[PDB]
Image (spheres, coloured by chain):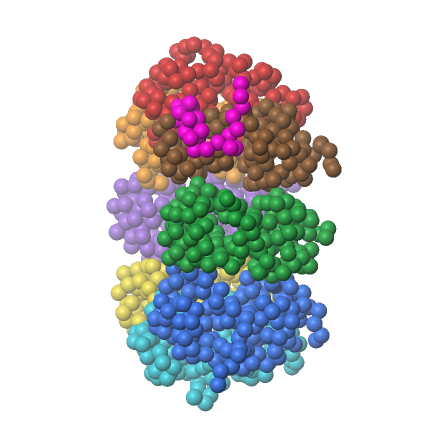
Chain colours: A purple, B orange, C red, D yellow, E brown, F cyan, G green, H blue
Amino acid sequence: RALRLLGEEVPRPILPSVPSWKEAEVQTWLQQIGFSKYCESFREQQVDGDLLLRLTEEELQTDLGMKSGITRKRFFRELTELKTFANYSTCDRSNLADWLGSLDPRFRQYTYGLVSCGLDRSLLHRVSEQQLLEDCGIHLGVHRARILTAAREMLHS
Amino acid sequence: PILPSVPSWKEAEVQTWLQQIGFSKYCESFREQQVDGDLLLRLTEEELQTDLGMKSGITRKRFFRELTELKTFANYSTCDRSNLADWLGSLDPRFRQYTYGLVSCGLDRSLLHRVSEQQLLEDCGIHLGVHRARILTAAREML
Amino acid sequence: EVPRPILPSVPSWKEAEVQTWLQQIGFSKYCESFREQQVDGDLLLRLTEEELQTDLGMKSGITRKRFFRELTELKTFANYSTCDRSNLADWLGSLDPRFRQYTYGLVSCGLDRSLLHRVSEQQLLEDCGIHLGVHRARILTAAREM
Amino acid sequence: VPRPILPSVPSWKEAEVQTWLQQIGFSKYCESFREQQVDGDLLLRLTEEELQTDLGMKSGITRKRFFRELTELKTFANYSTCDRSNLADWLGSLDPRFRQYTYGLVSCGLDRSLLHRVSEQQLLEDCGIHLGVHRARILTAAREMLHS
Amino acid sequence: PILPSVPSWKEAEVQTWLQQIGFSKYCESFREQQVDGDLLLRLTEEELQTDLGMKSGITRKRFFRELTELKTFANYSTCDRSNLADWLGSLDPRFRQYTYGLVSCGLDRSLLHRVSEQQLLEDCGIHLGVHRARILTAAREMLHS
Amino acid sequence: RPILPSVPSWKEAEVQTWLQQIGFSKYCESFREQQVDGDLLLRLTEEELQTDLGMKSGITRKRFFRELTELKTFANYSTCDRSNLADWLGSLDPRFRQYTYGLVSCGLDRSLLHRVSEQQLLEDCGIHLGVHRARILTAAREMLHS
Amino acid sequence: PRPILPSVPSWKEAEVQTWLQQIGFSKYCESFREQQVDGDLLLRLTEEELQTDLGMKSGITRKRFFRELTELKTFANYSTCDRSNLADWLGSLDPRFRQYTYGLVSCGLDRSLLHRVSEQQLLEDCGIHLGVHRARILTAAREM
Amino acid sequence: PRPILPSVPSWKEAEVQTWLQQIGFSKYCESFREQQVDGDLLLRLTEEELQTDLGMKSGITRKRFFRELTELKTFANYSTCDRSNLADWLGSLDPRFRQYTYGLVSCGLDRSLLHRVSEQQLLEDCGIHLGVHRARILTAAREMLH
């Protein structure tokens, strides 16, 4: 029953609908995770839920002014947590979230990446390593390999 | 309603659209650079950054988000004799956005079968590998 | 609203006719550069991105795109009879009207109908200036039959 | 439960990192580590690049001294919170010094059952095992592991 | 008319030619650099831009247009024992321009059969692939003694 | 002329003394500032010597490495060398003893040596001469185990 | 007139100086003097050395220079350094190949060793830059 | 007493200085002195060291220098460092190969080991830059009596 989601540490709300978040909800989340210093940049750049989920190292450094690699790592650590527990129902008709989660709960974080390229359960069998890296933004080879393996052993008949 | 005929748009219609999507700040650049429908549909990251002065990667992403919407719900009938728009749309509504890319290289339904992955990327401007692969696959099996 | 004359003998154009065409397509701003650089028909037909940017001072990629849009139109409807003995223009046009634009590129390398069968992909790209892969592939395919 | 023998570095907060820096004679860097908000997780995952550029440790020699201390800490740390399959003891059985790679492997979501499928590239790029000799030994031993 | 013996041209004849083709502007550079017939025939894009100060790619294209004409209608007899000029010309009049490139490497009719594509490009300065291919083809269908 | 000096356990002060003995007192300050002890001395690279210790001349670096090689040849490695690789390397060629710390720092011992590759001896262990690498590798494949 | 069998390998600075005058390169006498160019160095001169060390900035001027040097190399006496008379061997193939003598003998090649030479060796070690020349020299070397 | 072949491996700074004077490189005496070049370092000198550390900016000057050094290397006495007499072995192949002696013995090669040497080793470890030379030395090494 390892549910730290009922803990005080974890940002509120739990199970948030990040894809539909607007600037204001992004602002709230930055405060909770101790990144208030970056509120102004995120506001100016008009980061909403969709952009937050799609944020890259490059955008974070150049457009949002987060110069430290260590600070970016802290940021992505928080964003990965958010992505892991987010509600993707609006954008995830085939429930790729659960498919990824069944492989490993920490793979749920890739949901928006996969649905953003127009992948779904039916198409997943045909996905390539290149696609998972370039299109879906899965940077860890270990993760790519596991997802790829499981995708090839899917029943599409 | 009726879908706008973006391929035939002039500078003035492009200006109107920029206002509607909250990109008024860029009206002057678009005017100076004489962006019409054809050029708007064919706009690249590079042109947006260097020639139109949109320095932020995030702002460009917001812009392309709006442009993709426009491309998705545009009327291509003047330039799309074989109705590639509907073919793409039937595969996935999101693929309609690639209509102008394909017709600009002189592709139509009949020629589509012969297209390569490189061609869809370099010539047609389809950047997502997933999209390329699906379009390629479907093209070979209509043959 | 199409620039006059239609169906022009662009290969034989001098500086003056290039000047007139620039006016018609709304590029009067560039008349001075074209004049200074002494662009005639032959040079206009062979103009590259690089020459347009560096030597003619067209700094914007979007402006260059507008320019090439107009140049492509001119090339598509031009009369190549003086330089195209084997009528490659009609051969290209029969494949797709849009391919007629490549006429000068092919005849400038000394290609004709009879030699076309032997041409390579590299040759069409580097020597003939056919930049679109789709176009190269179609032209290559049709050339291998004849 | 006051003082543990093997420190729970994965669960360390900024303050414990600060204390450790003092003990190892790197007080000079306390401010940078504080400003950059280095906790246990970030300490364990620190790279050459971060140390030089973000923490301002310009000398390669100074960085070597730092990593000498970090490697010791990593070798004797308690990973129980984050290491369900006890990869620490698996690595340790091969060579005590290899226990230092625990956090690198568990951070990618590797465990004993997944070890058989791991590639040399993955050990280098994803897990941060830079010494070829170490990679080769770990790879060899992993080939005799049972998968699912 | 008379075909000029460009291989044997001196600076003065090069100067005259520049005037005739409307490149008087460049007379001084060509004089300073001591361009004779041999150097004129062997002139590269690089030399034209850097050493002779012809900055514009368009201007360089105009120049090479004139040089190609000259090369097409030059007399190569002093340096072309085996008459490669006529062999090239028979293939296509426009190929005569490559005479000096071939004879400068010590090629002749008898050696031509053995030549490689790399050699035609690097050693002989034939830049157009189409031209190279045609010359190569015709060389292989010669007399092989 | 030190007899079996225990360089792996040397502190800053012993490194300082050594620098004096070999006529490199000029570099005492940098070595002090950088806190070079025995372990760091044995693992010193060309890069660290140039950039961190301010030894700009390649010729001076060569002189320095000539002295370091001597020290490494005669050092006592007993604290870090449980399988006595030092004697094994020395028996092959006295000049190979200098590679002891490179090998034991990667956790190698007599029993493991056979599995090492030429790339590993270069990249991991710092054996720069190919001739040396090849000889060590060959002898390692033919050695007696338990 | 045109010098008969000059012993360029044995030339000293003074002879190099004289030759520069004769070919109309007096402007460069100072550089060649300062750099102490003798016969051996003249025969081994590279594009790089000519540009950077001798100050001959123009590619066209360098081309003129090498045109003269090639002539000199073609007519030189190599007897001091060419025991097996590779000069005459090369010359018999084509008079223009004589220019490569010093390149070959400087690597310690002779008639007897020539058969074993590789294309790479002729290019990198001997400084024969023209492929056409390399190929012909290689061919003839295999058949003697 | 004066030896015929100089014992360059054993030369000290003072002998190097003398040699520089004799060959007309007095201009460089100061640099060589400051850098403490002895026989060992002189024999091992590289293009890079000569340019950067000794201040010999001209490639032509460096060529003159190496011309002199090659002669010295060819006729040097290597007996202190060449127990198996590789000098005579190389010399028997071609007198000019004797110049590579110090390169070979510095990697710890001798007659008995020579059979095992690779092309890469002769280039990278021994500093034999001429392909022609490498090939001849390699060939002769393979066909030796082990």
Specify whether residue E14 is painted magenta.
Answer: yes
Direction bottom: furthest residue = F3
Residue H55 picture location, percent across and down? 37, 64
Q: Can you say which quadrant of the picture contains the C terminus of chain A? A: top right
Direction front: furthest residue = G1
Range shown magenta: E1-23
**Residue closest to the eye, H106 or C64:** H106
User: Relative to residue F79, is residue G4 depicted above or below?
Assistant: above
Residue C8 picture location, percent across and down? 46, 12
User: Relative to residue G128, is residue B46 depicted above or below?
Assistant: above
**Would you say residue B4 is visible in this rendering?**
no
Q: Is residue G9 left or right of residue C57?
A: right
**Would you say residue H139 is visible in this rendering?**
yes
Direction top: furthest residue = C5
User: Relative to residue H74, is residue C32 depicted above or below?
Assistant: above
User: Relative to residue C82, is residue G143 depicted above or below?
Assistant: below
Q: How many marks?
A: 0
- Residue at image location 64% in from the left, 24% down from the top: E90
- Residue at image location 73% in from the left, 36% down from the top: E144
Q: Is residue D108 left or right of residue D52?
A: right
Residue F110 picture location, percent across and down? 58, 79
**Residue closest to the eye, C96 or E129:** E129
Q: Quadrant of residue D47?
A: bottom left
- Residue at image location 43% in from the left, 88% down from the top: F2
